Length: 331
Ligand SMILES: O=C(O)CNC(=O)C(=O)O
Ligand SMILES: [Mg+2]
Ligand code: NI
Ligand SMILES: [Zn+2]
Image 1 (cartoon, protein in one colour):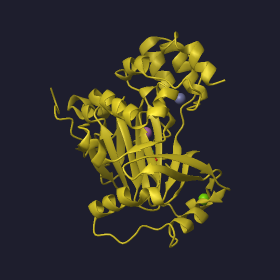
Image 2: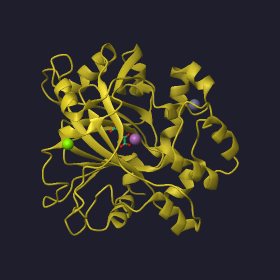
Image 3: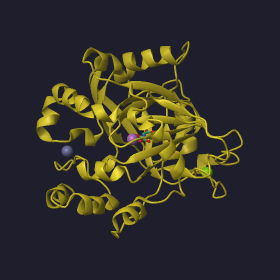
Image 4: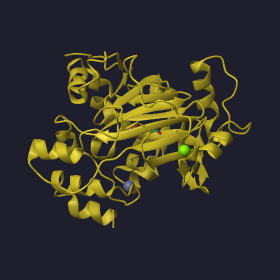
């Protein structure tokens, strides 16, 4: 078995290897990369996502989210308070302000220490989930707005024909902006490209051990657990590496820098934070190996997680028994 310790693997494809996305994903899995839950892909040196970022300030963040924390430093939840719209120019200036900027630090490790020590005492503002793309249309390799769609994967593998579309999303971060512990909708893959700015640190639990993280989360957030049988789908809970180590949960960590892709694999729980002002682009995708994960994915039926138009069809086809009760939560 390849990669039996479930380490995060790092790939350096050549420009020739960067032509066929699906094939490269299947290559990485042949080497065991999926067992970690997360892989890093460093693009060929000749590749570029776009020529410059020189006019991005005009993008609008229609609903910036202030991430307010509750709990203790190592075990907390966050709630997203909606703020008034602002441009990316305005957001970048806010990120660089004395109140919000990255503190002095020695290296990534000292910064990670400061994040876990101090996150809960601040409320950074996150521009999340903004439909759009920053890839140039002329970028033909690994362009996240030109991927094969999940609906087309389900049609090719299973013959079924469903509504829905699959488009990317932009994320604008600042110091301390946080993504809570989650897997993707329907336990899909994700791919995330860091277009610019400061790094993003990731934590991940190997898919084969996801249920260990779930059981810890039920113990740490016991009222949330009683409220919903899949409350990590709400994307609000944080657990620190120290707490994971104290409780024996297998995990890994890695820092993504500008210019790098990350792939998350089906049922790979992940969480993380941004080091400073940055912009990422991400999208879900499927392969044939996903289908079984989609059939088995948990769902939030409490109604909090409230998910997309396109996820309806996935549930309807892969989880027809749940269909009914899940759409009661989504209507
Ligand atoms: O970058 C972020 O804030 C969150 N992204 C992801 O969870 C991802 O790409 O799957
Ligand atoms: Mg602009
Ligand atoms: Ni994710
Ligand atoms: Zn729920």
